[PDB]
Amino acid sequence: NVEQIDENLAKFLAERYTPESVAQLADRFHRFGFVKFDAANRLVPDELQTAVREECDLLIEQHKERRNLLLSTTGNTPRRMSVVKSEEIEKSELISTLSRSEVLLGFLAGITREEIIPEVSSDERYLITHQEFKSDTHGWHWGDYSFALIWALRMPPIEHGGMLQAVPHTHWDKSNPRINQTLCEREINTHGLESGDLYLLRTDTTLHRTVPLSEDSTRTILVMTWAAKRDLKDLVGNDRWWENPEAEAARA
Amino acid sequence: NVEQIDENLAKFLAERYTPESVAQLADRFHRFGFVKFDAANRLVPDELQTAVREECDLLIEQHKERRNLLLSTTGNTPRRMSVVKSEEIEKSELISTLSRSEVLLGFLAGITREEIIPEVSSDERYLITHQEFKSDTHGWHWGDYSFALIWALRMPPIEHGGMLQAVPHTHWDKSNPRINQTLCEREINTHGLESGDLYLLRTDTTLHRTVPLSEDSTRTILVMTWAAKRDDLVGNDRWWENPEAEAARAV
Amino acid sequence: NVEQIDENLAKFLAERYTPESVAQLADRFHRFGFVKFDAANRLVPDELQTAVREECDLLIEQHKERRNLLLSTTGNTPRRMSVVKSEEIEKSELISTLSRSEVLLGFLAGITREEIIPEVSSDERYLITHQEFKSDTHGWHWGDYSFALIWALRMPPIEHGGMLQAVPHTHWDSNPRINQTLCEREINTHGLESGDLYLLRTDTTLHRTVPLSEDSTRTILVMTWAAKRDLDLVGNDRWWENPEAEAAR
Amino acid sequence: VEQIDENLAKFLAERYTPESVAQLADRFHRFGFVKFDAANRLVPDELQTAVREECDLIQHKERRNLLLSTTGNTPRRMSVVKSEIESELISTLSRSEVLLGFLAGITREEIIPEVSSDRYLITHQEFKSDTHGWHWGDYSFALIWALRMPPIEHGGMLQAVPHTHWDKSNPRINQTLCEREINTHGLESGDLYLLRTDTTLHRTVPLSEDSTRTILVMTWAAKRDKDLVGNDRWWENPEAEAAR
Ligand SMILES: N[C@@H](CCCC[NH3+])C(=O)O
Ligand SMILES: N[C@@H](CCCC[NH3+])C(=O)O
Ligand SMILES: N[C@@H](CCCC[NH3+])C(=O)O
Ligand SMILES: N[C@@H](CCCC[NH3+])C(=O)O
Ligand SMILES: [Cl-]
Ligand SMILES: [Cl-]
Ligand SMILES: [Cl-]
Ligand SMILES: [Cl-]
Ligand SMILES: [V+3]
Ligand SMILES: [V+3]
Ligand SMILES: [V+3]
């Protein structure tokens, strides 16, 4: 009921978090560019995530688009997955209002320590990626915007791959990504996830990817992309492979 | 696959459990009739559970059977669920071999503090319950056998119901179940479950049930029933194998 | 300090508590007659605790009075400890001001769910108990007043004893029936660590401290408060302020 | 009374598995440090209480206040008890084959009690500025008994830098700190920890006020462990030239 969702989520977060504990999560987010909301520290009520997982699962069964390309602006890292564009996820009233919820964005703003602005490009507001076959992966890349709340809806067993790897405190130079060079100079943090987890990712300064699936499994995530004040900046690269599969940077 | 699963499991358990921590779990088992293996205290590797889940998913879509009955031997409590009979689950080489694994049965024997014998009735070796609709429930009852390892494969949101309620330290008298009377005299322990959890249940002396679903959802579990040394079957109440058993009532 | 204690305590508590989580503490307080403020639920900043403990250490060395009698109004339960009188602790401006602090009583009122009135008897306003030898205990008893905030300033290891044992939802009678109540009810034992604070519903919770197994230091501070029901007093058993009370033995 | 190796081998067998100990070995090799706390006890609580009582040997309480030259003039401000300790309880457990056998699964190599009889060390820091300054160890292994630990807000934590080496002529202390990160290990009363004392630069943080920090060191040795150089040996001989 939108207003009832926010009123409940407010109580839900007030039952689990305090200003001191959020400040500890803010420290972790700035150190790793990543904070995980697992069974210990939940972010949304289990009934709410179920509702989100069902609305996403329906969008996959109808709108799934296979992608298998290389993105030149990220050192030609692979993008082997199925996607659901943002223009089609925006039809879901639940996912659309929740991604602009004053309660959710305000709570997470305590972790980012800066205003979270739900005003990003229409083709990037929401993204659903669905990896099914072996070698499927979201290759090393950066995000155009500052923040993204990722819903780890369905994750394979950790022995099948699919983990999130991350290198924080970097930046995206599209004219020269230096992806493999950065790995040589920095330690990689591997973040395993379990079905039901959510995590906040600082997408613009954290080089990240998903470990390829070593065997046929199912990896479904929902991405809510948000902006910071620094992102409100012209979009460059012509590398929007999730919307346009034959972008000027998408080589196959 | 095959006998390599016992070696993987023997390592999986050695990495997490010690005789001291198992003895602590054994204390909880006798106190509650219930020990939960959740995200903190896993029991089987994630890949192994996924393989068991996928085998049960297929068994459901292949040989599901709807049950909607009351059981006279358990005070006419409702059984409202779909099931897959033990005869069909035994077609799974993985599930049947894992139900008789010496390392799995051996580890759990430290929690039961007694030998776990994998010799039970052929219509009760395995069982799958599939609750899908509102008011679906596995009503108040006991187990004819002592032990049951329950795989909480798919569990609905906690706000929709489906929790295990239990009353430990009771007994099943099929001529006078005294279920509602036991509730009046004893406290009820409610056990929330999440998808992926397993739990060991002392089914003969723990009055238990699943909280009915408050809305359409999905609740899928697998039952591995084992026997103790204390375990002749009476009651004519084997409703999961025979929907028209003597004790099975209608409406 | 003085008026700085309130601004510091209000800022300290507002960062570690929400009205929703305080409600969860209020449930636990009505259930067990007891709620512990430990490393997971701090109540005062570390500086305020140090100043209170440091002040309490001086009051112990200067004016220690040992008690060792049996109280008839609590079934002849033993009271083997050293104590410091209330009028003595009232001289400390820090303890007296913190005892009436609108921020402290205001926060704790959300746990009791009723008004906490700092109007009690002059001889029972504050209390320090120091047990140093074996077989020392504050025997089974109740409280004449509703609420008491206890400062577990120095607590021995659990293996030495000194834990708080409690039976909530009782009352204090001419006929205490203490061992009978233990037979009919079951006892909650609450272990305490150095620096812990806990709120106790003293009028309805039969409570004691487990006797010391060996020589060990056990130092606490009681800040007794009252509720609306505590506004008529009897017993002739005020042993802490009068060791020659009519109930002592 | 030789009844310790039996009660210890049972105490450890029900609290550790070979795969659990292998995880402790990785932690020991990476940090040079493995702490035995409430989650991973090493001795029964009665045995430690007997050691804490036996050590409380301090009968030999000799204060120290020097600067060791082979460690860049880092301070040594504490009391000591000389290896006086060789009490039959500490001596028997130090050569206990069950204890040295289990701990060898963490070091991944055999540990030998054949060390200089100069063996056991009891540290007793009391006043402020008391510290066991930056240093290494002439021997590989040492099991430290944090018998009594002040609260963390006062100091006493162990700061360690693994994967280093001791050059008595050029200790390179502050320069090593600039190039390596410092691991701070907080300790509580009752914890024990195994320390690779030769390749781990370590120290205790100086106490911020008068407190009580009591420790017992049982220095063992390894096969790769030579000659005693530096003329340091400050815990034994207070006037050993290498002091200050
Ligand atoms: N730029 C990202 C896509 C961002 C989608 C929203 N976080 C990539 O190359 O995969
Ligand atoms: N006795 C149980 C059936 C157990 C089947 C699984 N072991 C009941 O009446 O519901
Ligand atoms: N009346 C209590 C002591 C109360 C002290 C003030 N709260 C007793 O008999 O021990
Ligand atoms: N060699 C160390 C002392 C070790 C004493 C024996 N465990 C130092 O220079 O401080
Ligand atoms: Cl991204
Ligand atoms: Cl059953
Ligand atoms: Cl009282
Ligand atoms: Cl050393
Ligand atoms: V991304
Ligand atoms: V009292
Ligand atoms: V040393």
Image (tube, coloured by chain):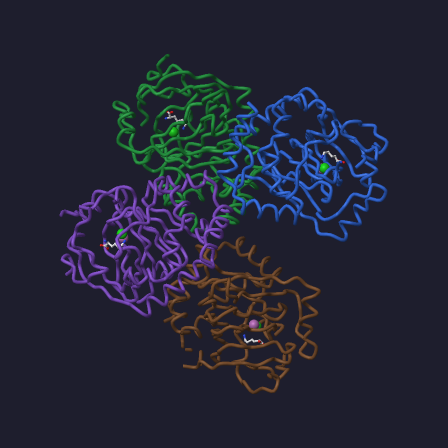
Chain colours: A blue, B green, C purple, D brown
Q: Is residue B1 visible?
A: no
Q: Is residue D103 above or below residue D135?
A: above
* Residue A37 drawn at (x, y percent): 58, 39
Work out whether residue C13 or residue C182 is closer to the camera in this orientation and state it.
Answer: C13
> What residue is shown at x 41% (from left), y 70% (from top)?
D51
The outermost residue toward the front is: C3
| Res. A110 in view | yes
Give above or below for D20 relative to D32.
above
Residue D128, above or below C117 = below
Work out which residue is located at the far top of the displayed protein and give it.
Answer: B251
Point out residue B43 in the picture as x, y percentages from the top left corner. Answer: 50, 41
Residue located 16% across and 62% down the image: C244
Q: Position of residue D75 (x, y in %)?
A: 58, 77
- From the viewer's perspective, is A15 left or right of D56? right
Report the image quarter containing ligand 9. Answer: top right
Q: Is residue C133 shown left or right of residue B46? A: left
Residue B238 position in % (x across, y down): 37, 21
Q: Nearer the viewer, residue A34 or B244?
A: A34
